[PDB]
Image (cartoon, rainbow, N blue to C red; front, side, top):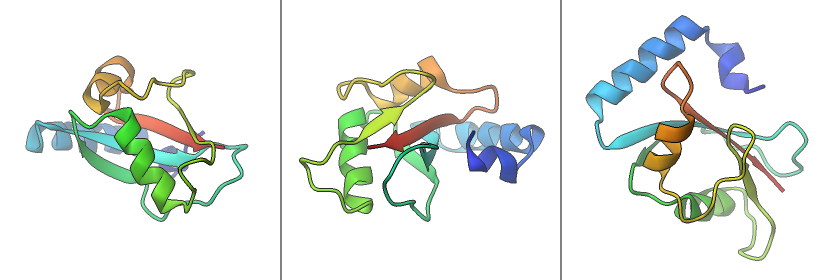
Length: 110
């Protein structure tokens, strides 16, 4: 599973997610890591605070660039056993998929 969940016990993650949701009402907290079997670069930053209206497609645009993919290279997000559509907003994805620690978890893969 996600490295972030190894690096921090549930109770602390939940307290931090609560904190963020209180402090930043129009942002959604996202943990982003490479999928276990993906063959692409790792990012140094895993904790994201993105506008709720940001689309999944825009988030691909940002992630793709940070891992030095070309627009024509494949990239997928895995979110709770699904690939979200590009038209979904991160706010929508958060409401549908956030964990009980109040984070949304997104894996990326080629």
